[PDB]
Image: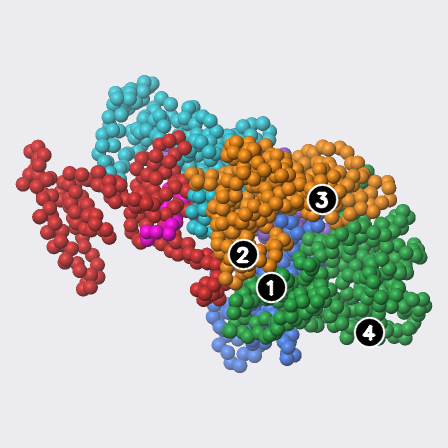
Chain colours: A blue, B green, C purple, D cyan, E red, F orange
């Protein structure tokens, strides 16, 4: 997979949040999970997993606003500057260093998607209950839904236009048909609920 | 009935006028460029500075002029293939003192706590040229040692096909008289030798970007220093290269750069040796052509030299503090 | 409808908010609905819906204020900038990308106006609850007024100067005369209310 | 009403608030309402009614803080800029188009003042309860004071220096001696209050 | 009395607060009442009465702080820029215009002091109860202390170091010895308290 | 103050390039009262521009502003091979000096023979007095120091003179600095005298703060020297007040207070360099 863009350096590249630029090519939206490869000087690789939430464009090369805006259409040296922000989810190793500005950033779609959504921690019970923009199901920890680790479900939103009751039926349909209960039942070892 | 603006740059030289450099053997053969495998290409530049002008008299009754000017040279290393980014090989800070025939002494400096400076001696022409006593020599000295510095990293010269240039170098402006043996390439920017003829201009404006004009022979006579008496008459090889198609409003002659290549008289070996460079320059400068929108001088510039020249300004300190330091030294 | 101008790029064009410059000719005021097209690199068109709620004019080409205003009126190179902000209502495709700075913006007159006010969710009960700045009625949903999903109508404002009872009567006149009840009642299929 | 200045365009001239520079001659003080006329592209004139709420003068042409005032008094060419903030109260037509920079501004006392104080909606019951800076009586509304539209009178402030009772007696004195009781009496139509 | 300094123009000279400079001469402290003369273009004079509360100096001519500070002592072109702010108390006429930047400002010590402290308003009962920095007693409205207009006395401050009980005795000494009660007694006209 | 908008280069069915420029120049005056009754004021500042084109004869002197942009379409003949870089840098200053003297020639105090009338409205010009001014009562001040060293004894007394006093009037033939082959009348006569404004900084050269003035007079008139005798005493204290204090401007000595504010006023009279270049660029393509 070709890299969408490159990490900017003019803005701060603090490990918590870092800006990056996108080269002419694949578009970048909002709430899309991406991963960047970082090479430490010693030699150990580091990967940062995060999701974008703020995107923007800026017309560079023009100084006086709306005076040469029509001139650019006819004849003027001008271009665009497409960039976006990344909020990191978690780091593949356990350390906090800023990514080196000048390294490529690429989307996560295979295994790298799994570590982004903490699919390794929740492996045996990976209950799908949603789909992202692309064809990748979203895993839900069934251990939190049931009493194995505790938790409930709370759907909130504006009444009417927001389809609230549709999600409860969809989760009920997915739980009772994906075989999640059957999988968790195995390896009981005399558990309290093994049916 | 056609008028347009043509990009040009001139700060130091005066009364350059517009001349005709045409000597012999101009031909019209537009040939496309092909990239070649070379390890590294070096682009060098220099920058002069003026700290403070001086004026002293020492029991003579006649004034003399001096200056505390500074000059810094630097080089940038590029890989044409594009494996990694560029790197600044070296940037060294140097200063000069240009005083008339008065012979000052004590070239020592002591930093009280904060500031440091270099003090030395030099001889501009041993009435006298007052205002220009340090505006023309300091640039002359700056290019003198810059060529000497560039002469150390140089690819081995080849007779006809002995060896390809391992480390190419590139110099600003015309090639100087000092460099005669090193494998160097210079690029000029002045447009005072543009109009070759009625037909030559017609083909020059109509050539597509990326190709180079055929190599022509120049006798480098008129531009040579008067009464130089170095060896007599030299020979140079020149060819034009286009970087862009030029903006619609700009003159069609924009985006055309002329290069120099010093060669021995009727050698007949160097022309076969620099034939690869003629094809190499077709695509090397196309990548090195500065894209228009960022810089005020949209054509007629290079990406590394724009960042390089700003680097020299950082190598020397701010103009205010150095002036404050020399002011304290003068009274004491 | 001819475009009223291009999109400013010197200021951020984040998909939520994007300034646009208005060309000479038509003038745009506050609370006007406009749409912009955006060519996605894949070729699929993208449309943004929003309403202007901030307009300004700036005098370009003056160094010190008010010392050349009389000079500008007589003779001096100056400029006037006519800009306007947009808060986007909804994006036609379900993605969030920044529009390209340099695209044409046009007012909504027909079906584009309906898609801007989410009228595609109102097919049986399209209720004219007043008139806009131009000669297009504002269609509201009668479902949110009656008891099919719950929800009353609340009118507020200071009395005397702002007539409140008159508008309440106007709404009642529009309910009984437009025949929206008949369009809701038809196709009851055992509905609780069908009269 | 001669022209007093020009509409400054250097600052934002959004329809809510816009600065304007006062030419030498007619001075402008605080709380002196002014009217700005603007020509729309179609041909319809537009007028703005608003009262100033902030004034300032700037000695443009110097940069050193309190170092050239002695030089200015003795020998230096410099000029002062008279700029005043204007906050609008209501627009002449029902549209929000910012005024064109370079317009002519003038304070009006004739019919134009009636739209400034919303005197159009109250003609038969006009109550002068105070005086403005010029020969201008401010018309209150007697509908709010009495039970026609409901309301009372509340006077507050620091007791002593503020002569509250004197103004209260003035309102009572003005009610009886201005005929406002008589004007409402005509056209009673069998109303509750006809005396 | 020679003018202390000049009114600044670089900062805003809004009638509420305006900066001013002091020429080489009489020093200016804090909480000193000053008056500035303003000449309207028509011809009517205006006087602004106010007290200073913020004063400052600034070393102009030096850019790099503490690097040339010692150099100024030995050999360097540098000077000072002494300035202060004025909070206006009240304007002699009733109009709010900015003072013209370039007119002199002088202290108030004679009659001009009286209008600054509203001594004309409280003429018959001018009870002195404090002294300023110079030899000018501070007038207190006895009509507020007693029941003629209402009011009490409340002394607050940190216990101990702040001499709280000393002020109560001083006011008691001043009231019973300045003859304020004797003066207010005259012109009784059958008043409730005329002893 | 001269300005340079954009250099031009055209070829019209000739095969040889020609050059042109769209430069600008603005003059201005400031009125002061030496006694100090009121502050100074700017009498006039007018915007003017010139086009310096070689022998190609362009036409159509028309300009139209679509909405915002105003500029002037122009014409003039610099020298009717050709000077490449300096065909519009020494020309435009020359024309600026020509009309500035003409503009200043209108407000002029009546010239007096010996004691006919005192100068009612004095004028002051930058640099040496030009050859055009021969009858008007004008005073010029130079700033360059390429003629400072008069001699061994002259420099010794020049550095030792206190501030505020003026050197005695000397006679100059102004022939060497005059334009070659001027052929106007030959060699004129000028009256010069030095004035000191400050005592000079300790670090800086003692010659700092010394200004040379010019006063054009007819040859051996013997009346003007008695007439400008008051000006010789007048300039002793006039320039002392005009001398800028040595901490505000970068060129702290050898300067004037109003000229620094005046030159900044010229830059404001003309618009920003960016917008004017944008307009002429659009006009060129169309």
Q: Is residue B309 above or below residue E136?
A: below
Q: Of the residues under marks 2 and 3, which one precedes in the sequence? A: 2
Observer-side mark, 2 or 4, equals 2
Residue that label 1 marks: B57
> Disc 3 versus disc 1: distance between alpha carbons?
32 Å
- The disc at residue A128 is none
Q: Nearer the viewer, residue B191 or D152?
A: B191
Residue at figure coordinates x 42%, y 24% from the top left: D110
- Answer yes or no: are tags 4 and 1 on the same subunit: yes
**The residue marked by circle 2 belongs to what chain?**
F
Observer-side mark, 2 or 3, equals 2
- Answer yes or no: are tags 2 and 4 on the same subunit: no
Residue that label 3 marks: F179
Q: Nearer the viewer, residue E104 or A1?
A: E104
Percent across and percent down for residue C152 are 44, 42
**The residue marked by circle 4 belongs to what chain?**
B
> Disc 4 versus disc 1: distance between alpha carbons?
50 Å
Within-10-Å neighbours for mark 1: few <14, some 14–19, many 20+: few
**Residue located farthest toward the bottom when viewing the structure as drawn:** A189
Residues shaded magenta: E10-27
**Residue located farthest toward the left when viewing the structure as drawn:** E195
> Disc 2 versus disc 4: distance between alpha carbons?
64 Å
Q: Is residue F239 above or below residue A56?
A: above
| Mark 2 residue element | helix
Residue at figure coordinates x 78%, y 36% from the top left: F58
- The disc at residue F157 is 2
> Disc 2 versus disc 3: distance between alpha carbons?
32 Å
Q: Of the residues under marks 4 and 1, which one precedes in the sequence? A: 1
Q: Nearer the viewer, residue E177 or F195?
A: F195
Percent across and percent down for residue F142 are 60, 48
| Mark 3 residue element | loop
Q: Is residue D156 left or right of residue B91?
A: left
């Amino acid at each position: 997979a070709d890299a969408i863009g490159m990490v900017l350096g003019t803005e701060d590249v603090t490990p918590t949040v870092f800006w990056f630029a996108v080269s002419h090519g694949a578009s970048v939206g909002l709430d899309d999970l991406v991963v960047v490869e970082t090479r430490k000087p010693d030699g150990t690789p580091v990967r940062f997993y995060g999701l974008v939430d703020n995107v923007r464009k800026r017309h560079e090369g023009v100084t006086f606003e709306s005076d040469v805006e029509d001139v650019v259409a006819g004849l003027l040296p001008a271009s665009v500057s497409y960039a976006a922000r990344v909020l990191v989810t978690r780091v593949d190793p356990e350390n906090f260093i800023p990514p080196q500005p000048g390294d490529h950033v690429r989307h996560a779609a295979g295994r790298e998607l799994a570590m982004a959504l903490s699919a390794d921690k929740m492996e045996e019970a990976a209950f799908p209950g949603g789909l992202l923009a692309d064809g990748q199901p979203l895993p839900l920890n069934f251990r939190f839904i049931n009493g194995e680790s505790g938790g409930h479900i709370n759907i909130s939103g504006i009444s009417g236009v927001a389809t609230k009751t549709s999600y409860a039926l969809f989760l009920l349909h997915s739980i009772f048909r994906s075989g999640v209960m059957d999988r968790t039942a195995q390896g009981s070892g005399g558990r309290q609920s093994g049916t | 009935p056609i008028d347009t603006f043509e990009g040009q740059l001139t700060l130091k030289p005066f009364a350059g006028l517009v001349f005709d450099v045409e000597t012999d053997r101009w031909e019209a053969i537009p040939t496309l460029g092909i990239p070649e495998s070379v390890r590294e290409v070096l682009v060098v530049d220099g920058k002069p500075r003026m700290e403070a002008r001086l004026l002293m008299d020492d029991d003579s009754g006649e004034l003399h002029l001096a200056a505390f000017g500074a000059y810094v040279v630097g080089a940038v290393s590029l890989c044409p293939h594009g494996t990694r980014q560029a790197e600044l090989l070296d940037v060294r800070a140097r200063r000069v003192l240009a005083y008339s025939s008065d012979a000052p002494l004590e070239p020592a400096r002591l930093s009280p706590r904060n500031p440091h400076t270099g003090v030395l001696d030099y001889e501009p022409y041993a009435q006298v040229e007052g205002p220009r006593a340090a505006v023309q020599k300091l640039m002359l000295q700056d290019e003198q040692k810059l060529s000497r510095q560039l002469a150390s990293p140089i690819a081995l010269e080849e007779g006809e096909a002995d060896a390809l240039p391992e480390s190419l170098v590139l110099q600003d402006g015309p090639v100087r008289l000092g460099g005669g043996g090193s494998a160097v390439v210079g690029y000029v920017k002045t447009l005072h030798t543009d109009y070759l003829g009625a037909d030559r201009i017609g083909l020059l404006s109509s050539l597509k970007c990326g190709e180079r004009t055929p190599i022509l022979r120049f006798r480098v006579g008129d531009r040579g220093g008067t009464f130089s008496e170095a060896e007599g008459r030299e020979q140079r090889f020149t060819w034009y290269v286009r970087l862009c198609d030029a903006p619609f409003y700009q003159h069609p002659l924009a985006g055309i750069m002329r290069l120099e290549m010093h060669a021995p008289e009727d050698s007949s070996f160097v022309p076969a040796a620099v034939q690869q460079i003629a094809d190499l320059s077709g695509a090397l400068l196309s990548k090195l052509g500065s894209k228009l929108h960022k810089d005020s001088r949209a054509p007629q510039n290079l990406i590394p030299t724009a960042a390089l020249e700003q680097a020299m300004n950082r190598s020397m300190g701010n103009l205010e503090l150095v002036t404050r330091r020399i002011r304290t030294h003068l009274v004491t």
